[PDB]
Length: 16
Image (cartoon, rainbow, N blue to C red):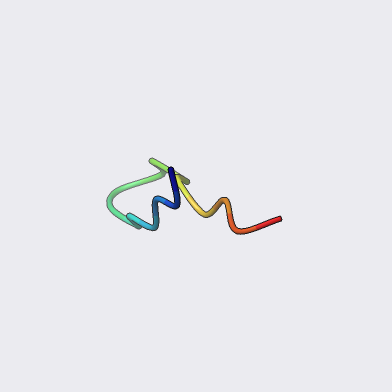
């Protein structure tokens, strides 16, 4: 369920 990815303006940080 958790997802964390940071690229060239591609935020994908989700913990909750």
